[PDB]
Length: 71
Length: 429
Ligand SMILES: Cc1cc2nc3c(=O)[nH]c(=O)nc-3n(C[C@H](O)[C@H](O)[C@H](O)COP(=O)(O)O)c2cc1C
Ligand code: SF4
Image (cartoon, rainbow over all chains, first blue to last red; front, side, top):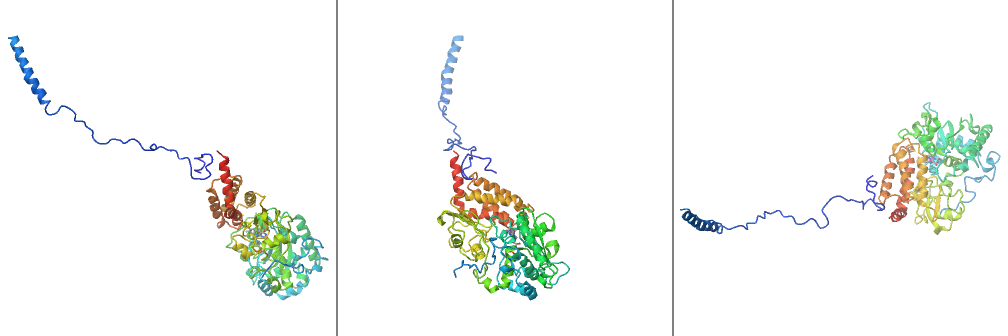
């Protein structure tokens, strides 16, 4: 058998049997990423302290002015 | 030397074509039963010795050296009456050389029964006529009744002191029953199924009694071998192979005929001289099955200079069986012819052993596919391997006789098989 299970009309020979099974497409798949691409594009060490310090510098002045208005 | 030329005074089987009377008053004129009393009186050892010296080989497919075969029979009789079964039955495809001895000079066959019987210490001869040879065994029973009435056979061998009687058995249409170890059984009354060789017929054959199975042509040339010269007989053919085989040019020759002619004859010479010629000239030849049907093909490129003797045809990757040369010309479908041969071996295979019983139906199926082209280019190597699985393993040589036609067809005409397969492939799609 095995030439009556995989017919492929013609083929003249036991080789050239159909042989259609699963696999990667011709040319493989896309290059798959595996590294750790963690983007560190956030606020830096400064700009976070200076936003906090800047908020403290101006916002506490605003607390003071609000205390003046309340008084 | 250069063989082939056999003069009409050297042909052993005179009245082959039945032109003259076959029976007595017509056989004594041809030298039959001439002085067999002296021969029987010359003894058994002298007969065996002259048969061995004459180098007579088996006229049947086996090709065994006769005489040496007759020396296998026991000398001192231990109560088992040594028999002598004559293998009249042929049934080989192509072979009619037996059919021209059973009729048309059967008295040579009866005198050979007697001379081989005294030769191998026998006590009775069972001429196993092929079943279909009804007219032939009727002629032979007529000649047997004659040789009984003429005191030749029975209770005194031609007036001598030898008690020897010839009984005529006849099978019924079975090529397998013709085999040496199956003749004994098909004559013992059982089915025509061969027995294994470890008990040899010379040791325990017919009825368990010793016996030797001889083709009619070997037993029938025995008389004239002894009455003429064993040196004269061995003066024909090549060194080892010697004698005058009775050929049967079977098919696709413009004048098919069975004609006795010296062995070691060039196959081309035989064809061109006696049977006329390959239909449409020698250049029209396609293949030739030189022996019976139990022998591979000859593809016409090694058939020009091949000699019809056992040794050369065996050296050409073939065999000289009953020398029933089957000729096939460029007009035949050689694969269909070998497919019908394999069908024959499927039909006439007593089925006793598995390698032949099954693999021969298998060979027939694969051949009836490849003759259309329904196979695959690698099956031609399965077919070779299937045949080599059948060949050495079967009980008798019928396994051989069924693997050899297909093996020869492959070995020689593999281009034609592959061409049919590729043409089937291109016919699809
Ligand atoms: C495959 C096969 C085919 C045979 N064909 C024949 C045959 O056609 N004629 C015959 O007389 N004996 C035939 N025999 C029997 C023996 O092979 C052999 O021919 C016979 O027993 C003795 O013949 P011989 O004394 O000339 O060798 C055949 C045997 C086998 C195994
Ligand atoms: S199967 Fe073949 S070899 Fe075996 S006994 Fe039958 S014919 Fe002979």
